[PDB]
Image: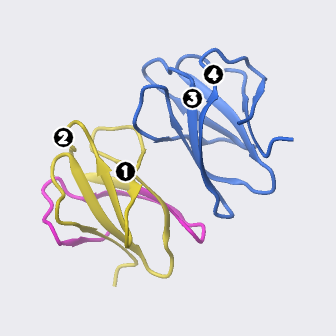
Chain colours: A blue, B yellow
Amino acid sequence: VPKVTFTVEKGSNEKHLAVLVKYEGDTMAEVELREHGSDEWVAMTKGEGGVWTFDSEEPLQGPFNFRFLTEKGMKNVFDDVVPEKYTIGATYAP
Amino acid sequence: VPKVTFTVEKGSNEKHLAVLVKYEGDTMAEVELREHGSDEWVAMTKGEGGVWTFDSEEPLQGPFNFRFLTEKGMKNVFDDVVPEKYTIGATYAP
């Protein structure tokens, strides 16, 4: 079974993305997002229960790339993990 | 003496900022920058020896705000620490 998963949450739309991130055996310290066509890693906001969110004034363009840091020291980049046309409630894994 | 300091490095200009960050007794895991007038925390790139850099296509507008995460678990935000008109080689502390 995949060690890192990204589950899209209800409420996600063009200007709001909420993602439940899970790394087996560790917890997220910081999660950053890079939308398709962007060269910048922008910090996501830590929500409750492992959910991380991002609010934008312009439309968000996928596929989405995530970069994170865990509390035990892991740092990783996962490219195009969440597709442009994602489905609410589905789990994505690299 | 200040516990956290930000020293501006040679080479820093309108499109390139290099900052030596130091937190006594800890080491930086991630350092993010928010320029004046921005609502986004963008990740800086880890250089050698504690220096963190940021390259932009448009001019960088200070004062600069920094948000960081240390290897031992500290997370902090320091607003307007580096002024718009900074001097190369000078140390800034909150």
User: How much space separates mark 1 and mark 4, taking CA atoms?
Assistant: 28 Å
Left or right placement of residue B48 versus residue A51 in this view: left
Q: Earlier in the sequence, mark 3 or mark 4?
A: 3
Which residue is drawn at the image coordinates 74% and 19% (left, top)? A88
Quarter-wise, where is residue A58 in the image?
top left
- Quarter of the figure with the C terminus of chain B: bottom left
Q: Do the residues marked 1 and 2 share a common chain?
A: yes
Output the chain of dot 4.
Answer: A
- Quarter of the figure with the N terminus of chain B: bottom left
Q: Which residues are magenta?
A: B67-94
Q: Picture coordinates of residue B64 (x, y %)?
A: 28, 52
Q: Picture coordinates of residue A44 (x, y %)?
A: 55, 40
Which residue is drawn at the image coordinates 67% and 20% (left, top)? A11
Mark number displayed over residue B59: 2
Q: Do the residues marked 1 and 3 share a common chain?
A: no
The residue under label 4 is: A83
Output the chain of dot 3.
Answer: A
Q: Nearer the viewer, residue B2 or B61?
A: B61
Mark number displayed over residue B84: none
The residue under label 3 is: A64
Q: Nearer the viewer, mark 3 or mark 2?
A: 3
Q: Amino acid at mark 1?
A: Leu
* Disc 2 crowd, CA 10 A, few/some/many (<14, 14-19, 20+): few
Q: Do the residues marked 2 and 4 share a common chain?
A: no
Q: Does the segment drawn in magenta span residue B74?
A: yes
Q: Picture coordinates of residue B60 (x, y %)?
A: 22, 44
The residue under label 1 is: B33
Q: Nearer the viewer, mark 1 or mark 4?
A: 4
User: How much space separates mark 2 and mark 4, taking CA atoms?
Assistant: 32 Å
Q: Nearer the viewer, mark 2 or mark 4?
A: 4
